[PDB]
Picture 1 (cartoon, protein in one colour):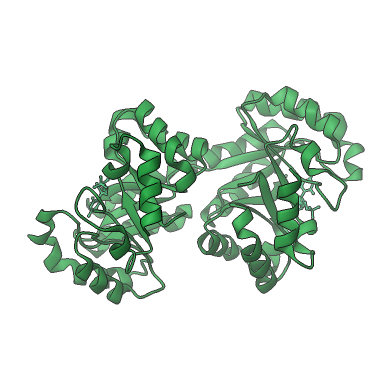
Picture 2 (tube, each protein chain N blue to C red):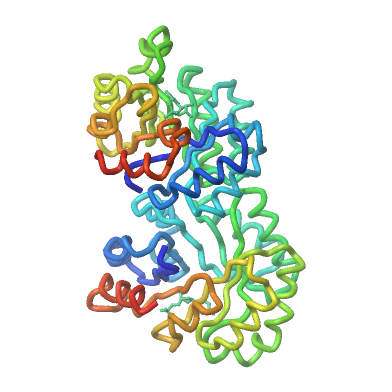
Length: 211
Length: 211
Ligand SMILES: O=c1cnn([C@@H]2O[C@H](COP(=O)(O)O)[C@@H](O)[C@H]2O)c(=O)[nH]1
Ligand SMILES: O=c1cnn([C@@H]2O[C@H](COP(=O)(O)O)[C@@H](O)[C@H]2O)c(=O)[nH]1
């Protein structure tokens, strides 16, 4: 909805529920990561899904060996997540393990190819095109790419095709622009610009109207 | 969305996709049953979920022995359904088997307590209150009750409490009224009044505005 995904990284349940409820009319998809899950428990995923009737993407940056990745994905989907974000840099076998569980459980894998922060230029950027091509070869249809580098987002879009779904973080606080990012991504992920705002609903409304 | 769930019982993929796309702005939840699945395959569930970004309730009226019920639910959730409708009349063990799989896969079970058609008065109605109480005892939080008998829907709402989620079919073609049904149910299910209409979008819009 509105091509906007809320990155809910507040660490306490009450604040997370308050902000998510305030901006629900503008979204239908919430990205929940370890900051909230490690503080309040995996049960928070089912609670959000039920209370807000939104889709939940678990941003767990899965980056282990195949066998452990299988275990992490199974627990995550058992908890009710609709999709999970997985790193591609640990290799194809590690990604395939995630895809196997998603297939078994009727869920989806998002492949993270290039990250949005400054440090991403050190090692990830140099491998990003190859990671995206690996995703295509494995049948991945959902990807994550950087708002902070639209030229890289364009290159990623080029590799994955127009039929793949691409979401992009780094919007707002990290420097990314909503409109420019949406020239290439299907949806933008926004965390701090909304959840640290004095009026999260007004902040979400502003982003939606700017695009 | 709009407390309206589309019962997509057309049997061919092209017509089903056309009508669902035409009314998508009014809904966010589609009920898919055997008329469409047995004609086009279980893969239609993932296709709808992806193409329309809606939640999918599989109306499979699960009504077998525990072991078979477990198999049916597993295949259904593997196919991507968010929830499954199960009959309560075959007993508690049969329902528990469904709840066990839903727990394993992070999904939901809707318990059907009293049906909406005339024949429901023969045997189901007499057992309906006990079936609803069984659901409460088993921890069921989602229920299906009849639009065609609001006094029975009221009795069912009484047993399950205000915190349980109740959806109700029999609206329109079978005689049920949207507004009266919503006095007790959280959402109404509508099939033919929308999918056989000359203008499904206008029909959906009319129902939404009447409530
Ligand atoms: O390359 C990536 C991948 N993931 N995220 C995540 O997306 C969200 C962005 O939040 P922000 O809007 O507050 O910067 C956070 O949950 C963060 O972990 C990034 O920021 N960059
Ligand atoms: O008690 C019940 C349970 N399920 N349904 C189902 O709900 C839908 C109602 O469709 P309709 O609006 O076309 O009558 C159909 O898929 C039907 O199998 C009923 O009608 N009554």
